[PDB]
Every structure is written in structure tokens, then in C-alpha cells.
Image: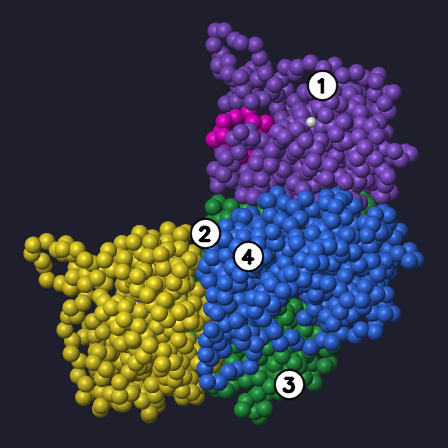
Chain colours: A yellow, B green, C blue, D purple
Amino acid sequence: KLKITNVKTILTAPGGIDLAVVKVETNEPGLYGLGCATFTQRIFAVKSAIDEYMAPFLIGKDPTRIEDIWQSAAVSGYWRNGPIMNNALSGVDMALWDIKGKLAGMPVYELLGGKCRDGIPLYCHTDGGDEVEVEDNIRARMEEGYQYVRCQMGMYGGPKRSPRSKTPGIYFDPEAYAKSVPRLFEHLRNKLGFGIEFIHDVHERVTPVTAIQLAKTLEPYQLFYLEDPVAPENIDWLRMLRQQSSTPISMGELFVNINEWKPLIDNKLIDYIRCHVSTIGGITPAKKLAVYSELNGVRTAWHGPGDISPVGVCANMHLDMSSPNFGIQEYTPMNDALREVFPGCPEIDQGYAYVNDKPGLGIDINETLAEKYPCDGGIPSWTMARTPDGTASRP
Amino acid sequence: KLKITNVKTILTAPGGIDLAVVKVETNEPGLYGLGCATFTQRIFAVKSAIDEYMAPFLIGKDPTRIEDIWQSAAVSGYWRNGPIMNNALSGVDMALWDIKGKLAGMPVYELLGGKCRDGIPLYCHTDGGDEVEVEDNIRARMEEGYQYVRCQMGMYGGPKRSPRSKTPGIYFDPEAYAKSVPRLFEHLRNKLGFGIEFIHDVHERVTPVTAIQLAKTLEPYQLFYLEDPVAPENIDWLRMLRQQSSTPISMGELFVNINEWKPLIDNKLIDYIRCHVSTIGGITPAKKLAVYSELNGVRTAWHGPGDISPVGVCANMHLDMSSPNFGIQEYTPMNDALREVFPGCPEIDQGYAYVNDKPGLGIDINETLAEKYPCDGGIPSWTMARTPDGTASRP
Amino acid sequence: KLKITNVKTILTAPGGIDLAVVKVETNEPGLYGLGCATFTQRIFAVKSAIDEYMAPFLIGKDPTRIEDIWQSAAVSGYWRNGPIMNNALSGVDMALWDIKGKLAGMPVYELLGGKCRDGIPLYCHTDGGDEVEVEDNIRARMEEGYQYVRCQMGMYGGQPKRSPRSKTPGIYFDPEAYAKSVPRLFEHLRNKLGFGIEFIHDVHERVTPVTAIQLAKTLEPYQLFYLEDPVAPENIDWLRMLRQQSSTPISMGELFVNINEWKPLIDNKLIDYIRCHVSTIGGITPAKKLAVYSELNGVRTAWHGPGDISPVGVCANMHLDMSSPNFGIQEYTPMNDALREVFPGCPEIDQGYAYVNDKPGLGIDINETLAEKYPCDGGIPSWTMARTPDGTASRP
Amino acid sequence: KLKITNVKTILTAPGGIDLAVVKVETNEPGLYGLGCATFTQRIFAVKSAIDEYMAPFLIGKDPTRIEDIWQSAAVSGYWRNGPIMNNALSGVDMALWDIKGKLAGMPVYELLGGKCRDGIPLYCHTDGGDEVEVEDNIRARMEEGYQYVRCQMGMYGGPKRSPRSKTPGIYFDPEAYAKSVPRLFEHLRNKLGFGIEFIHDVHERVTPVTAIQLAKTLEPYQLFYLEDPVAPENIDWLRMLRQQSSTPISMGELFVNINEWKPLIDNKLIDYIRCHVSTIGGITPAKKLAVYSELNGVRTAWHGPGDISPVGVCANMHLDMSSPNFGIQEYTPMNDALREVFPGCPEIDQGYAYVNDKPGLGIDINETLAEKYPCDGGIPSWTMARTPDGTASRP
Ligand SMILES: [Cl-]
Ligand SMILES: [Cl-]
Ligand SMILES: [Cl-]
Ligand SMILES: [Mg+2]
Ligand SMILES: [Mg+2]
Ligand SMILES: [Mg+2]
Ligand SMILES: [Mg+2]
């Protein structure tokens, strides 16, 4: 008797970043579910994938068969395993989980095993043009109670002279950046000590052997993790990196394929998995990945940037709450508009997030207010990255 | 405010086999859980492990924290990873899942992802003094609707002449056995054709190279799987077997340790994992193992012998209904007394089991009728197996 | 026509810790064997395994067929390889070896190959709340003649992280604070005590694998005798990575209960010392095989010798130690007068060496009347409920 | 204080084959041990090694420290690990286990674990000029109760025409031999069925790839094992063989070095280990090897040819009785002179050996009687083996 009746996409940008949220409606009045489908750079293609394909696929189906729906939806177009398609899956799969919590009168984290911890430790971003400005941010965050911070200085060497004419793009200098990082952590550790945990994100910006040298050279500074030392396309290089360095490694925010993460985890080539939950297809595959990670002694560090709706932020945190091998939660602070469009955002208190104990994902969306923040769209400029000679780089 | 108030063990043998069942009670009316702790050969030590250690560990705690309770209970005695300790964990763990289901008003399979299939295909046992009587039992089961059957002939050579005086034991002949099997199956395929699926259990009765030769020789007869070709102590020999044979392999009913199954599944050394759910610690670790197997393309075939309670049977089947990588369910038909003592046994109809949609595991125990069948105790004769020269062997 | 006539458990706690000892009686009056079955956290379940299962299995059987009995008892329940079941095996196994030595008029170490050394070097525990207390305790043990010491400061960090606003009960620790703190501790010890003294540190599975690898690398200059339990049994695959990078000697194994745990480690040279609790792997018979397998791979023995092992198990450790060419070290926990009185025959301790007597079998007895005067406490220890700062239940 | 007072070597040939036996005497009345040092082709050098080196090394030492003495003697001349050195070591070591047994009042097998089986299954040799005389020898042995036989025909081809000149030697033809073996076994299996167990010894006579083909071609004939398909110098070729063949393999009669057997056993490259007990250093090292093998699921098959003293026959069998992984025992019938010179020979009855229950090794030597059978000495012809072109080969 219980059936899905409609599946819609809501495009909104209350925090200044384009989000896509899927609402799954049922034939029981007042019962619906929400999921995150935020691939911010391709939101109009996610909307199209949802509206043209997922909706007619799902109408009339029983929403509680979460796994049957996930498996059959994922193969419905034959070709599969990519970010746009995975996000259409995630919008729906999170919405079904959310519905299931509502039917059970339980938060999703109670369905997945119950609380494994009393609060969810967070890290946040601290930027700076130089060593002194970065420290200032770290200081401001420490006073708010963060015990973990990600430290970047500048924009990856944004130093060598270019040729006499340049093709447009955002120019960076990988070797300049690579030499400056150790100097940054020497300063920070000297200034602030070793109580505070540091994360640094290489963001696939240097060649693999440069990343290996960096990992080795940062060993004295004891990072919580070094993130993204290679692109997904270069993951075989981690065999060599892990023969030589003891700095903790994270990878995975870019992953969209089991053949990317499985070999890393099987071989202990990373210490934290960083997948963007919606980008791997939602709660159902993320839970599986978390378990695979757990048995291999690898911990989770779900991607938590600004380009994730509060619905996905709840999703991450429900997974965090119920995972024994939870590592840490990246967190990007929200504005008032986001909290008003999405009542139920988790409470943030002194470096910890406390999720509410409302049923499902414990999160709502106000469609009326959402319409007041239409999406910008447009090509981001920062993904056009060039090295000093003008070579287009993975950004 | 919800609390565990009592934990007790019930020993009963309605089917003529010593069963152990754990009841977990709470301070909410009508809200309790049952789980299976059946390790039938050490039932009195499992009772001691539950009564002396688990029960005081649990009284007063929040039963919804299934993962936290499982993790902390499993390390409560420091040493861990064994069949008695695991069965004590399982009795609690399945009971906590049973309780969660009741709180949510849902079958456990609904909590674990929902229905993946319309029914659970079963296999049953068929024995016989010879190729003629085995074939008669196979026909009988095919009339009842079974489409998969396990074929054994005799008791593994129970032939070389023994020495002049024999030390007591159940004597078998591993070489006579191994030669006779391929003839068993040549006869069965000629008789019955290739429509019916056949399983054969080596039960660790031969040397590893002998099992490899047996697996190779049975290839033409196309077994659904060849079970336990090696003892858990000899798992490294499966590397050799899998370079040479294409007969599908199941392993794991004896497994109690992740270091036993993780290497085999990681290297594609088996096709079906056979763990006895309570012996690995219950639904919680069993679900993780199902997922681990899933990502590696290995399917489940949970142990379903006579020495498992109807509660453990229901756990198997709830795992079976929510696993996309479900392989097959071994089934031992129950007598009237078992169905009377355990209200809610799955319905068995033409080779399929159909679970009820009742909340939790959908199963209960009548404590008064259970008392009419006290456990026998004693040590089984069959675990004292000797080869022709008198050597004590892994049964 | 020698036969086993009865098998019984004695549960006693003369040193404040609960012990289980097995007595195997025969139809030869006065001839019996004693074995250690001490799994202290589960002694009542161990007692049940022996009383309900081992007893009927063994009554009537010829006690001299140690290997046959071990093999047939180990698989008597079909399921096998776990701490309670191995301890019931061990109680019987050591008791049979004890009987064989009594029949032969020889200590067990004589049946296992005879003396390979002239005494058994020991290490003792030295703890402290801070660097100086550790060092003071070290100086006190050196004065008693100890030449190896295990050094732990504090309780695994329990500058610690702030926890969330409510805490679930448990014993709280902070693995990152602990990790940072260890190298500082050894730099102090070495600067104050020099390099003559041998140091052992136990990580006790308290940190993530890559943290332990970093720790092993950082400790290299301080030259530990061994770094113990860098990973949990569940994580042994991480030792492949640690052994590609660190030259700190490693020991593993007090938690081991399964061959599929230790065989790949030793085959691949992933550790330098095997640390099994002898009763927890099933007694002298399997311990001797492990020692031999180790030897051929160049790995040495360091059998677990905590407070929670009876003096009979201690004698077993030492008869194995006396007869192994690849003996590494023997952890020793000093006994009080009550242990010595309940178990006459305890080995002599003298200037960091232990000297086993030359009486037949394990050379140890039990005064059953005196044993009854120290009943077992029981209960659940609090320490195995360990939580990191956010509240997560941890491997203790 | 118990001390070794004398060590002498006794060379004798009661069975037509040069034997060496060591007697270690002590300062306790009636307390002496015997052991085997029989490297029959080099007996005179083995006597020199014992008389000039071992004897003075031992005098005045305590014979109960078997392991200390073994370890320290093994390295007493610095260089080590060879057949002559090992044999001198065996002679003392077996003697010391013999002394320990007499002190204990127990058979050596009781010191090593107690009885593991009720008697020792034997195999014997059956040779023949052709396929039909071989059969006749098999029937003869079957009448005497042997259930396992080793089947060879002729002399490994002893067919291409050789060059016009021929260097002296025993000529064979490996290519003709390889092609004859599978035909021998097909004939024998056709005539004798699969009740009787067959062994075949390739004796390092063919190239490695030829042995692999042989191993595969014989699979249908189901040998108990195929022995020595490669020379010790060619063990790396077993990796290839075991990827392709399921015929059980035995190796090791020629082994004298741990780096020979340890790789084969770790990697499951053999099923039976075939070492000559005295040629690896006696009971002490063989027992360690039996245990290393057991932990890897490999079974023992100690060398039991004519060039072993009945003292060595007794040591094989005391190992055989106390080994859970015993596989089979090769046995060469003794004549009346051997049984007269060596009182305490095992009783042989219908294909089983039954060792006496006397203390130590239960065997002794009549020195006066031994002197009536002096050692011929000399150089055997058979080890000068040539292929058709004249090439000196591994015999
Ligand atoms: Cl799609
Ligand atoms: Cl037991
Ligand atoms: Cl020599
Ligand atoms: Mg990043
Ligand atoms: Mg089975
Ligand atoms: Mg320790
Ligand atoms: Mg040979």
C-alpha cells in the first residue's frame, strides 16, 4: 500500500553556493523524505537526471525496499559509476532512509546501529595570505573550541616566471607551493605547539614524487592527516608513498568508483577515506564503504565542504554517529539563511556537533523560503588551473 | 529512560539437539528480545559465559546502542575471538536487534535495507548407504519442491586394513572416500540430470592436495559448491586450489576469527562464506561480513544445521532477505515440538522460506513448553574420528 | 594400565588475582599433574568447560598420550580455537606433561631437550605517573639486579582533548596525547640511565596503526629491546607497512588464540618476539610447536608473564624458556608470600634471573586446603571499558 | 654427575650395505646410547669426522643437554650444513635421545608426545624388467599385507642412439623413461584397481618441465605421491609445477640445508617431506622439521632405504609414532644378519611396523657380531649416470 508518488528537485543557494535537494513524496499524507544531490558544478544536469529518469523510475514503488531500489536504480541506464548519476542516486537513497527513520520513529543513526559516541568532533578551515594571518584564524577558531583545523597558506604558490604570453587560467606554482608547506608547519608548530591537530590539503597539486617528499618532510610536524597527495588517476603511486612515509594519509573526496577506493583500502594505502557521500551514491553505499574501511582499520572522514546542503551534512553525521571507525568531521559553518531554509541543522558547540534525535535525518526544508535564493550557475574559474608554463592541471 | 533489566538463558532440546537462547528484557511493557547462542557441544559453558559475565555487563544499559554494546562486550574479557565467547555475544546481539525491530514496528530485514528478494531458496540434506538410497532421498526432496540438495554417501569411508589393535574412535578412510565421490556424482547426474543443484561437503576429511584433486575431478558434474575442502588451520592451501580448479568453493562454518575469513575473501579464494552466525558473534558482525563479501563478489551461505535454534534460523533469513549477495540457505526441517516451543517459525513452501512481517525477528519462545525438553548433555562420539592407522583427525 | 580417574578445577586468588588450576588425578596413588587454565576474566566459564566437558572426555584414558589427547580434545567440540576452550586444553595439557615428567623422574625442560642456558633473564614492570617516578622505579629494580624493564608512564593519556558535553561511562584515555608523550619519556630515561639498561614499552593496541608506525620510527634512537602490541590482532595486516619502515624490534601475541593470527606474522618476519599467553594457546604442546616454528624463522619467545597466570603457568613459561634455543626474555610479576605457600616449588628469583628447581615435572605443587582460604573475587574489570575522548568504545 | 666418557664409531655391513653406528658411553652403569651416522657412500669420512672431532668435543659433558650439545656441535667447526657433518651430528644426537629414554625409563616416542597411532603403515619396493614382472612383484607384496608400494620399471631408460664414442658410465634415456611411466601406471591400474596405493620415484632424472608434464599425465592414476620430480638445485621449478598439477609431490631425501626445505614447505610446494633423518642431523632437527611441516599441513615420509642402520630405522619410527602429521614409512626388509647384529628390530606384520616398548630407541648392536661383516668400501657405479650424448647427470 505505501508508494512513492513523486520525486522532485529543489535547487537553492541560501549560503551562496548552489545546492540540489531531492524531495521524495509518498501516498501517505505528510510523509516525505529528503536527500542531498549536491554536485554543485553540474546541478542543472543532476536536476535533469532526477526529473527525466529517477522520477519515472520510482513512481509507484514501495519506498522501504531501500537496497532493491538502490541496486536496480544504479543499473537502470546500464552505464553507471559517475558523479552526476551517483548524486541522482544519493538524493533518492537519502530520502528513502529519511522516510524509513520517520516510519520507525527513529533517527537514521539508530537504524544503522545506534550511537557509538557522545558528540562528533569537527575540524574547520583556516586560511591566510601568510604565516601570521593563518595563525590568527587558527587562534580565532581555537577560542570557539575547535580542536582540529585545516591550514592552507595562499593558493598553492599562485615563484617561476611564465613565458612571454599566457593562456588565461588561474596560475599556480607547484614547486614553490611544495617548498613553502614545511616552512608553514615549522612556524605553526613553533607558535602554537602540538596540542592542536593540523590537517593540510595538497589537493592533487604536485607530481606524485613531490607528494612523497612532502609527506616525508612533514613527519616531524605530526599532521592529523595529509589529504589528497595524488589524483584518483594516480592512486598506484601510493604503494611507493606508503613504503617510505609515516604521515597519515587521506584520499577520496573525488572518488566515484569502487575500483578507485577498494585497492587503497585493501592494501592499507590510506588512513582515512574522504568520500563525498552523495557523490558515491548516498547512505547505502557510504555505510558499506565505512564497514569495508572498518575491517581494514581505516577511518572515515566524509567530505564536508560548503557545497553540501544541510541534508547531506545530517547524512554525514548520522553515519559518523553510528560508525565505530569514525575518524573526524570536516565542517563548514552555516549562515542564518541556511538554518532558516533547513530547520534542524545539527547544533554546533565547542568543536563538536550534536545531532538532534528527531526521526529520519531530523532535517526539513522550507520550499517557500528556498525559492527566495535562486541558483547562480556558471562555470567556476578555479577549476581552470595552470602551471607556470601554461599547462592545464588537475585542480 | 529505556533500560535492560534482566538477561537470562534458556536451554532446551525440542528437536533432540541442545539449544541455547538468550532473552533480553527491558523496562518497557512487552519489549524484550531473543537471540541464539547455540554452540551445541559446549552449551553449559555458553550458559556460564552469559550468566556470569554478559548479564551483569548489560543490566541498566540503553539497549538501542547495539554497536556500542557489541564493541564493548566483545572486549570486556580482554581476550576474545572464540566460539563460546562469540555465542554469548550473539545471544545478546540478536536480542538487541530483535528489540530494535520492535521499537521501530519493523522486521529486522527492514532495518537492514529491506527486501532484496521475494523468498529464500533453500537446500536440504539427503544421505544414504549407497548411490541408490541417496537418489531416493533426493527424489523425495524434489517432490517437496527443493531445487538444491546436499549429497553425501555414507560417512567418509566408515577401505584400508587397520593395525592389529585399535584405539577407540569412529574410523574412516579418507582415500576410499575421495575416490568414491566422483563416482557418486557421475551416477547422480546420469540419474537426475543437470537441472537440480548439488552441494557436497568435504568436511575437512582429506589432505589438502587430495581436496584439490577432488575439486578438479568434480568439475564436469557442476556442483553448486564444494564445501570445506580444507580445515581453517590449512586455509593457505586454497591459494593452490584456486589456481587449478573452477569448482565453486564454500568455507567458513568453523570460522571464529577475522584473520580466518578476510584473507580468503580478499583474494577471491572462495565463492560462498558459510559462517554460523552466532559463532561469529551475531547479526552485527554477520552483516559486516555479508557486506565485506559483497564488495568482493562472494555470496553468503550461512550455516543452517540442526544445531541452531529457530531464533538463529530467523536471523539467517533476515540477513538472507536483505543481502544483495545472498547465495543460498541451508535448511534443516523442524519437528512439531520445535514449532510448538518457538512460535513464529518461517513458513517453508516448495523449497522457499517465507519470513513473517512481524516486528523484530518475528520469533518467540514458550518458556513452559521449553522446559518439557531438558538438554541431554554429553560428548558426541563423532568428533572422535580416526584414520585407518588410529590417528586422531579433524572431524 | 595407567588411567586418568578424575579431573577437577581449583579456583584460588592468593595474590589478589583469580586463578584457575587443573588437577589431573590417576589410578596410581599419589600420582597427579597440575596445569594452568588461568583466563582470569572468564574463570567461571573455564571451570564449566573443564567440569562439564574435559572431565568426561578424559576419565579412563591413558595420560601418557599427550599429543593424541591434545589433538582429540581440541576438536571434541567441533568448533575450537578460542581463549576459554584453549585454557581448558591447557589445564589438562600442562598436567599431562607434569605427570610424564614425574613418571620419568625428570623436570619438563629435560623432556623438551634439556637446559639451553644457565638461568632465565627476567624483566619486571616499572610504572609511574611521570618521567621521574618511572626512573625512580627503574633505579629500584636495577638495584635488585633487574637488567630489563618495561616502562609505562600514566594510563595512555587518561594536553588531553576536551570531551563532548556528556560522557558515557568508561575509562577515558587520549591516544594522541599518549603517542606524543612516549618519545619524550624515552629521551629522558636514556639521558638519565644511559644505554646499558634494556627497555620495553607496551603500546597495548591503544593507537591507530599509522600512529604506531610513527611511534616505532621515532623511538629508534632510544633502542628499545622491543615495542609491544603496536596493533590489535584484528589489524595484523598493518605490520607489513610498519616493517618496511621501522627497525624497532616488535613483539606481538599476548592476545593471540589462533594459528591464522601468528603464522603469517612469523612466516613473513613481521615481528621479532612472540608473546603468547601459554595457557591461552592451549598449553605446553602448542607452545612448544610455536617456539620451534619461531626458531626456524629467527623469531624469539617472550611468553606473557602477567599477574594473571598461576605459579603453575609461570613454571610452564620457564620450562619452555630453559629448553628453547630461541628464548628471548621472560616477563616476571613478583609473587607475595601467600602464592609461595599455596604453590610450593615456585622458581627461585635472584638478581634478575629465575632459577627453576630440578624436581620432576613442573616441580610445582598446590596446597588445596590453603587454596580454599583465598576465594575468587570474580566480577567485571573496569579497565576493559576504555573510551577515547569523544566516547568511542576502544580495544583496551 | 652424569658425564659422557667415550664415543666410538662402528662400521659394519650385515645386509651387504656399509653402515655406521655411533655408541656414546657414560659414567653410569648400563647407560649408553646408539645412533645412526649412515652416509653409506662416504662412511670412512664420517668415521673420521666422529673420531677426530665429535669424540673429543663430547668427552666430559652432560649428555642430558641434547639441544645445547646439538647447537654447539653443529657450529663447532664454523662451516656447517652438509651430509658428512650432519651425519656425525646425527650419530651423537640419536644416541643422546637414546640415553634420555633409558634415563626416563621410556621409549623415545613417549618423550616426544606419546603414541599418535596404533602402528606404522609401510610401503615397500617392487621393481621389474617389464610391466608384467612389476605386477607380479606387487601381487607378492600384497599377499604379505603391504597396502602401499613403490613402482619402478627398469632403469630410467637404461631409446636414442648415442654418439660413435662413449665415455664410461651407466647410460640412461630420460625422454624414453618419461614416456614409459604413464603407460606403466595405466597397465597397473587396469590390472590391480585403485585399492592399492602406488608411489613413483622420478629421482631427479628428467628436466623440470618434463617432470611437470609427467605430474600432470599421471593425475588419473592417482598416485600416493610422485617423488623427487626435481633436484635440490632446481626447487624453484616447483612453483611452476604446483600451479598446474594436482599429483601429490614428495621431496627431500637429498636435503641437507634449511634453505632447501623451508621455502618448499612455507609455500605448500610439496605434500610429503622425505628427509634422511641422519643426513639432516638426527632426531632433534627432524622433529623440528616434522613440526614445521605439521603447521603447514605437510606430512612426513622419512627416507627408509637399505643405506640406513636399523638404529636409523628405529629413529624414523619413533618420529612416526609421535607425529600427528605422519604420512607413510618406506621400509626395506632386513636379512637375518641385520636382525642378529641389531637386537630390537621393529616387528613387521602385514604392512605395519610395531615398535617394541623398550626404553630409548629399543635397539642395540652386538659389536662382536658386527665385526664379522667388514665394510667393503669403494665407489658405487650407479652415481656415474650418463644421458645418450655422454653428459654426466644427477643420478
Ligand atoms: Cl540517473
Ligand atoms: Cl573445552
Ligand atoms: Cl663433524
Ligand atoms: Mg580536500
Ligand atoms: Mg558443513
Ligand atoms: Mg602487553
Ligand atoms: Mg627416492
Q: Chain of mark 3?
A: B
Left or right placement of residue D326 versus residue C230 in this view: right
What residue is pinned by disc 3?
B6
**Which is closer to the viewer, label 4 or label 3?**
4
**Which is closer to the viewer, label 2 or label 1?**
2
Mark 4 close to ligand 6, CB under 8 Å:
no
What residue is pinned by disc 4?
C190
Q: Quadrant of ligand 3?
A: top right
Q: Residue type at mark 3?
A: Asn
Task: Give how far apart the Cα atoms at labels 2 and 1 are.
Answer: 52 Å
* Label 4 SS: helix
Q: Nearer the viewer, residue D140 or B19?
A: B19
What residue is pinned by disc 2?
C245
- Estimate the x, y position of residue C93 in percent, counting from the top left: 76, 56
Q: Residue type at mark 2?
A: Gln
Task: Give how far apart the Cα atoms at labels 4 and 3 are.
Answer: 54 Å
- Estimate the x, y position of residue B48 in percent, counting from the top left: 70, 74
Task: Give how far apart the Cα atoms at labels 2 and 3 are.
Answer: 51 Å
- Estimate the x, y position of residue B334 in percent, counting from the top left: 62, 73
Mark 1 close to ligand 3, CB under 8 Å:
no
* Label 1 SS: helix
Quarter location, residue A100: bottom left
Q: Which residues are magenta?
A: D199-218
* Label 3 SS: strand
Question: Residue D44 bears which disc, if any?
Answer: 1
Mark 4–mark 3 CB contact (< 8 Å) = no
